[PDB]
Image: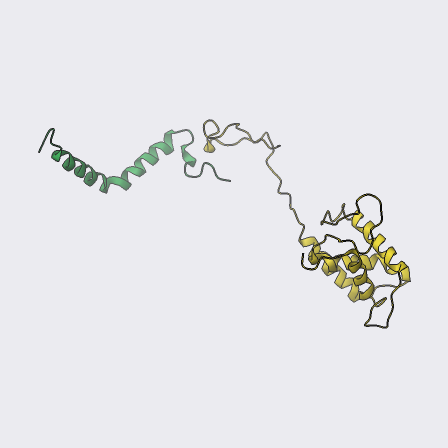
Length: 150
Length: 51
């Protein structure tokens, strides 16, 4: 994609959005808070394979370790949602509580992500339900009664 | 111009088309009605395969 999201960029976004490590609040950044953040992101993405479903995350192949310089594989349309969810999960490390505006932003981004993965399964006919004489089950098609399976 | 000479045949063919053209939409209704009443699946003809 456009510039390719790395796993370190997402955790830096989350750290910046609450004024923990950025150049436009005071100063500073730590190296352990990065490994902790990246591991938290990996575990979150593992969990998301259940409720929100797969979104294309690129996991580490074999054991090794994630490393912040690895390519995430996510489209750029998801970074705000992922970053806000990660910030919500990792706020309590520093003993902080989110403000209402942060919660509102997180909910809006999550809703945008949810809208892009809908299915609406569209239930089918049963299998003992007849198909009428009107569509000529003898000659044109075969098998009067719907299959309703496959 | 007749018998083997087919100059009669073009006149016959022209007469056929002249007779066919006016009574063209009238007979369609007759055929559709007979087929609508008698053919087993004929009441849905036009849709048949729709989904």
